Length: 295
DNA sequence: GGGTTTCCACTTATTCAACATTTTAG
DNA sequence: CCTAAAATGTTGAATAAGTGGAAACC
Ligand SMILES: [Ca+2]
Ligand SMILES: [Ca+2]
Ligand SMILES: [Ca+2]
Ligand code: NA
Image 1 (cartoon, rainbow, N blue to C red):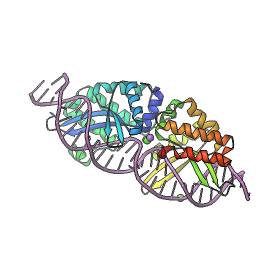
Image 2 (cartoon, rainbow, N blue to C red):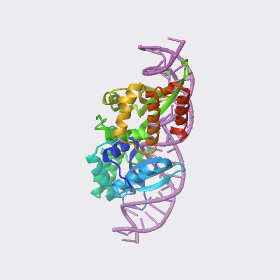
Image 3 (cartoon, rainbow, N blue to C red):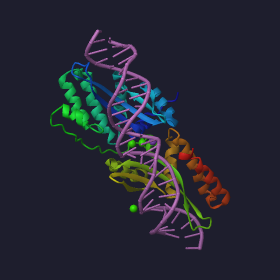
Image 4 (spheres, rainbow, N blue to C red):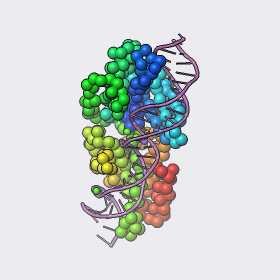
């Protein structure tokens, strides 16, 4: 029954939200197409209570299973989309997703004017959809023979505050205990790692985390044709003095919170040098077993 | 109406989270 | 030598993004 701070909500939407525009062949519509406009977040079942909390913050949206292991919050009821717009006007998005929101807003105006029931409005929705997310299907492009741009301006914005960061990290952030086989006396080095992962279309934002948080580095990764970035922090001093205090003051949501708290336990032990004792490493190992995929 | 809207079931691709090992720095 | 810090690479599923079907609203 708890609500979410609005900037945390926008950071979580930058991480996990998606805007939807359906343009559907419909034999019963006057113009031959019906439409649906919306916002949605799909998460693993274990984080259903986040969706319930967003739903009670906005008082809009419906929650439904999405397959066997996930669950969605979807807002497509047209009048309820005014809450979505009012929220993201007041607490605006930061990632390239802001561009998708701007297209969602253009689609909202077409629909608010009832133009989507006419030829000209459907054509404008098609032009808007061509720039949104994955674009037009081949079928829908062939149905609207017209030179239609798929290009948009890139978004370039700075992290607005640490609440946005707590929300974004609740989505994309990762805290772990990395056990490194070592030549140390004890034979296992404990490394705490904070990671944020993102596609390269938001390299600017990613690169800025180094300055925003005053620590870390960025790597690129390649998997066949796909590319993404990690921001990482591995220096214990930065973890303990910069990362941990941020998220104690700006509280994570979801089960990621419990992983952060467990991570902070191991930070305490390292600060006490108990990671260099057998009784310590044993406890660290137990804590790690119950984090992330092992929870 | 009956054209339009809204919801639920369910699918798809891949961008995330996750992870361990291997070097390097100091 | 002893630890800490950074780099090297994967992996596969939790995301993002999307479609089929139809009840029922206005
Ligand atoms: Ca994302
Ligand atoms: Ca995500
Ligand atoms: Ca490599
Ligand atoms: Na996530």
